[PDB]
Image (cartoon, rainbow, N blue to C red):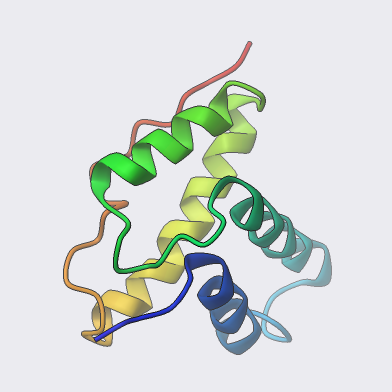
Length: 105
């Protein structure tokens, strides 16, 4: 079972598998994505997120960010959900088909 806030977990995750492992300038991205997560998805529990929820959060984000930017957010969040799946703590990867990443230009 996986009961925790999406934002909280992301930080937990990044500091475990990304922190000192990846480039410094690159880690900045995860810190940003973390920040974003805290904003667009406040007390959102990982176990409540649905393909729709996520797509919706992603849309709201796209209406104030560029495509490239919104993409980076998604991709990074997606990666954190993977280990959650692999570990067998999360049933369905809601970020799976939500591949739709609203643009801006």
